[PDB]
Image (cartoon, rainbow over all chains, first blue to last red):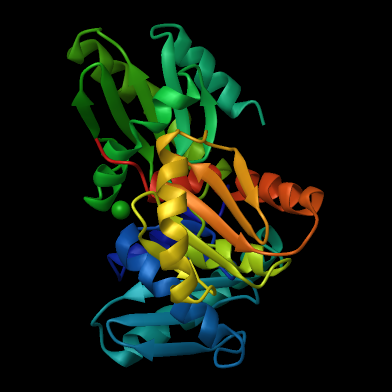
Length: 106
Length: 109
Length: 107
Ligand SMILES: [Cl-]
């Protein structure tokens, strides 16, 4: 049926703490608490102007950003090893970045 | 669309003084006089800063707060018993939480 | 964050403004502090008469706008009154309920 509830179960299969957000600040789904997201989003909007091209990730552990689509960003709080996180993102995209760009176009 | 209308009619079935607001303070629906409602906001602000969990309530009678989703707050003025109020909120959540969460997402503009 | 958007909204029409609390707390301001400190005792006394929430008070070039119980907008401007009242009505629609929650008068 509806994605987002599908994206979150995917992510939770390997990370407890995440958020699926849009570029303006809209949280579509999040297990990260509001206090952390409020201080986190201004940093993400900055990097979004030219440091995270669509399809790329950005690391500052425990925070990680993945621009799945042009408008949709995944935010992780994790200490997983790098290759696991990149692997999660690669799979998440190839199973979701089509449906997600279709449901949340810019 | 009609989600807030359905939320309102569900609450009005039991309490007459209520409001539904966003967690940034936007009033979506309120039968409480806007002046009286805005004076409960110091309490709400403290609840949100202490990150009261989704599904949890807070009682300062006659005022009652219920965090149905991350971004949607139910407010009551009521003298009804706590066990009835807590049942009302759990049924309210069951029927409307998922929809409210999609219709009213938290936003950090 | 919310105050940073308030500042940006105001800045689209006037450049000399301040957003303060009832007790005088500066939240954001492009007005020289020299001016604000000689301007606050006037605000305090207007607040006493309980200049109502939503109303403004003109003393050109100075304008006060009580957006919420606890938040005052101050402008130094030589714009016309209708333009100032229109900016205020717009400002209040976009920000008053948010501001009321972010900066509640306590007790
Ligand atoms: Cl929270």
